[PDB]
Image: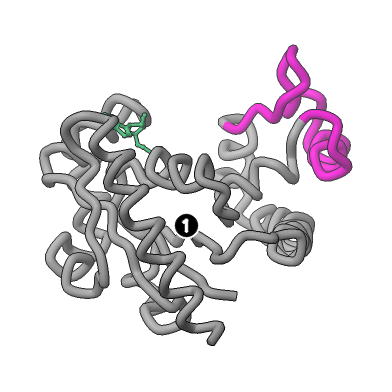
Amino acid sequence: TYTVALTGGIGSGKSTVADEFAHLGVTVIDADIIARQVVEPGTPALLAIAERFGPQMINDDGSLNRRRLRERIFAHSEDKAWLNALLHPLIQQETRRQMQASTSPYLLWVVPLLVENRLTDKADRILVVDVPKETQIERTIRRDGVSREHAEHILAAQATREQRLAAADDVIENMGSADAVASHVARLHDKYLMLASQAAS
Ligand SMILES: Nc1ncnc2c1ncn2[C@@H]1O[C@H](COP(=O)(O)OP(=O)(O)NP(=O)(O)O)[C@@H](O)[C@H]1O
């Protein structure tokens, strides 16, 4: 199936761009979303976490207390292997279920570390969501509650903005009016539709 990889640095707003494609009927595969889905309230995976580490892993609303789980892994690195063994098969299975259930002309894959992990060959096209470096820092501080210095360190550990732009087939700047960004998405959607038809012929 024709696949577009959506990449971008921290704080770029990849998910708001991906949502626009989803609104146009595109199947969006996002491993971070799938990871949260497999531990949602009532899931067997969440129960396994609670039965091992305790009921404090479940908030009053039935959801995973993510900070408590991060604290457990921080104190007991051995528990990272147990968590991966529990969750990785579920994420892989749900990823494949969503792929197989798709009926859209192409798939949009949200890939956080495409350039870092050097995956810029497996998708048919690469779409980079770009913002200025200061915009990344500002948005990461707000969403994640980190210092500017922390945000700068994360940027240092990721591919450079220039590397991402260099690898991109298309660039969408997640800046300015939201309506114009949505219009930009619709323009790219048509491009991908025609490319998917070309590939199928
Ligand atoms: N156009 C925008 N203007 C302002 N804030 C935005 C915009 N688009 C997204 N955001 C915010 O920026 C933050 C990052 O967006 P999100 O889509 O969650 O990031 P991501 O790039 O998908 N993931 P990550 O690598 O972890 O940052 C969120 O708090 C969004 O609400």
Quadrant in which the N terminus appears: bottom right
Place of residue 168 in the rendered image (x, y in percent of width and height, measured from the top left): 25, 70
Closer to the camera in the image, 104 or 151: 104
For this view, does 42 lie left or right of residue 36? right
Tell me which corner region of the image, top left, top right, bottom left or bottom right, holds residue 189: bottom left
Q: Which residue is mark 1?
A: 110
For this view, does 45 lie left or right of residue 133? right
Place of residue 161 in the rendered image (x, y in percent of width and height, measured from the top left): 16, 60
Q: Write down the region rendered in magenta.
A: 41-66
Q: Tell whether circle 1 marks a residue whose Cβ is less than 8 angstroms from ligand 1.
A: yes
Dot 1: element: strand
For this view, does 173 lie left or right of residue 43? left
Tell me which corner region of the image, top left, top right, bottom left or bottom right, holds residue 103: bottom right
The residue at the far top in this view is 60
Place of residue 3 in the rendered image (x, y in percent of width and height, measured from the top left): 50, 71
Tell me which corner region of the image, top left, top right, bottom left or bottom right, holds residue 112: bottom left
What residue appears at the point 24 percent right and 74 percent down from the top-left corner?
167
What residue appears at the point 32 percent right and 63 percent down from the top-left corner?
127
Place of residue 136 in the rendered image (x, y in percent of width and height, measured from the top left): 21, 41
Instruction: Give, as a three-letter code, the residue at label 1.
Output: Val
Label 1: how many residues lie within 10 Å, few (<14), some (14-19) or many (20+)? many
